[PDB]
Image (cartoon, rainbow over all chains, first blue to last red; front, side, top):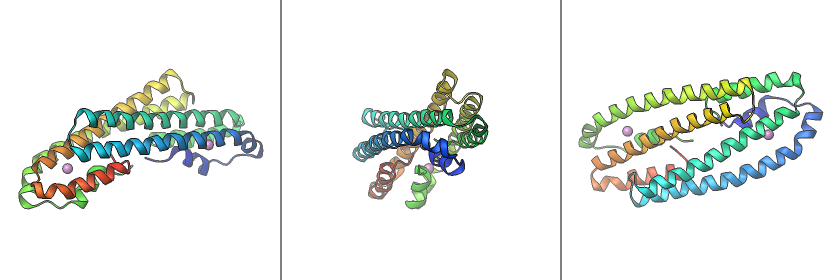
Length: 111
Length: 111
Ligand code: NI
Ligand code: NI
């Protein structure tokens, strides 16, 4: 359950050019992450509400679980695409440490 | 990212009869959880390995993400079914506190 994005930002320094050329992509990702997180929080609330009314694996509960999964999946994908687009801006020599952090975090289940 | 099952076990005391009549279900769920967790760890490793070879949203990476999602989803469902089967063994008077803990944890995204 680690925060893959935060892990990478904290663990892998960028050089001056790298920081500058990725600023716009970081801003766009922050906005996209917030939008999807709003959907995920709402979906979690709908699952909670469904179960509050009848705790059972019912059609309502099943559909609410799918909405949670879709929002979490959209966030996971958007996060990976952003990780990959950052990698493209890195100098080639700087990719091995970025990759190490990425791969290790994925292996532990971070998203 | 809270552990829904652990939250419920720690926060909601059971009476003597409740504890006794749920022991077999707890054992079965522990075994099922471990089996699915083994699959999830393996799937996380395969996603890490795929990205190690080419960090890109490629067919291999996409398929590995789906395997992670399927294992996580199987675990989420098995966990909820077990939560519901425990609820059935509770005395009716004991369900409101169980439900409170369940609903609050779901609202925060625990699974
Ligand atoms: Ni970033
Ligand atoms: Ni249990």
